[PDB]
Amino acid sequence: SLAEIRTDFNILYSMMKKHEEFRWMRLRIRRMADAWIQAIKSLAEKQNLEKRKRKKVLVHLGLLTLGELVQWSDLITSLYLLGHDIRISASLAELKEIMGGGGVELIYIDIVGLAQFKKTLGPSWVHYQCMLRVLDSFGTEPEFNHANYAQSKGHKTPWGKWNLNPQQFYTMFPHTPDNSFLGFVVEHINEIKRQNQSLVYGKVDSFWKNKKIYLDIIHTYMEVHATVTKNIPSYVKNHGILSGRDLQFLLRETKLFVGLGFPYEGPAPLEAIANGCAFLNPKFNPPKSSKNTDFFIGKPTLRELTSQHPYAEVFIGRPHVWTVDLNNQEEVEDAVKAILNQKIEPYMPYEFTCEGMLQRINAFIEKQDFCHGQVMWPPLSALQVKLAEPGQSCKQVCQESQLICEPSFFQHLNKDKDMLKYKVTCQSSELAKDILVPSFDPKNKHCVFQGDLLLFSCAGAHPRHQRVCPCRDFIKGQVALCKDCL
Image (cartoon, rainbow, N blue to C red; front, side):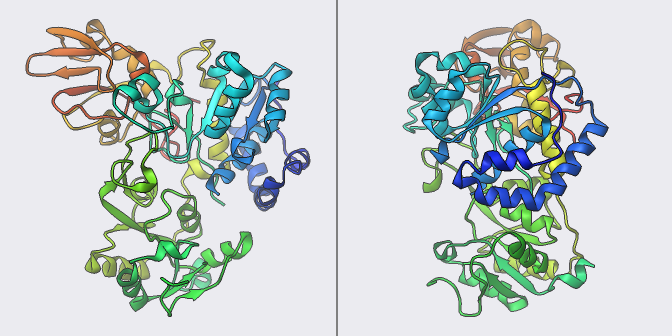
């Protein structure tokens, strides 16, 4: 019953061959297999992977009943290499059968899958609720997760309302500290690269609408390539749809990967950057959110995107990523001229490598517990308390101190005597059921405390008062983990 690392993919291949949708995933695993195997052996030599319980894990892919398919494939691969006993489900019948047999210790599921879980198991679905890890790309903020609070704020979305611990939501990028970051793995260079080759990001013609001036400025200094036909200028060199090795060859050859504004926060810009490409990242001013952008309306989050790829913008930056105003002709020309003169430096954040994803998912499996049976994680030693100004979120004040909001610490910040420790003295206090508390009015020294523990929230700025904010440190290249979290 102890987990043993796997160094051979034969059994995995056999399991994924049972569902047609895994076909192009198996190809990707074969291409990446040597990287995965070096990674699990390297992790096991560097960190104690001994004496882990082998878990029976349900993976229910609601969406099989894309970036999402890449994330599923990397999660399943990581679980397999770490030695866990994986039961894959892509039907209501498999789901019923796996849960029928009992002994399930951990459940990875998507939003569509979760509705199927509740319907198929009936009222005892809640018995398993603490074992759920819900793959949810764009994230779920606490305000939308709390069904009754969402109704009371007049949100009309069908999404959210699961009443989970919001750290059970697993995101594509570390954009929502209320949630956990799952992510995925990103699959002489002077000689290989065509210095004046740009490639447009966007496999559909619709994405190209109103980018003519932008594309013309790039075309002044570079060839414009595409992999896509009304909106496409005559000078564009279309290679058609590519795949695997061919696309990787094209990226290896490309100096500049050109964002058009859509799609939002995909894997492709990280793949370009890993291959030595610079990424021209459209800036969004004002930021795009469920409040101003049709695509985002109904998403169970108010999170604002400052660019097409906020992760690339904030966690990578120049020289790999140039975040520019598409409508600023001077800034676009300067960016393109600078990129042309840049030395090529292929870059991959550690959190998007095989080893970094294995380390992250291994820490969540071993340490993240909503079922009440394990010591506090992250450990309390990691708490650094910060006061957010009015109009600033807990997410914002941690980030501006090179930290990350840690929602599991909110419970240690929620009464008069606990505040004393953090040089805040409450002359008076009350309880509110609000995402914006605990709060502090520094004028009249009035503290408002959280009356509904499900409403603790890294998201949300108080218009008038300071917020009392739980921050933690993170390992550079591994934002999901605090220094003492391994």
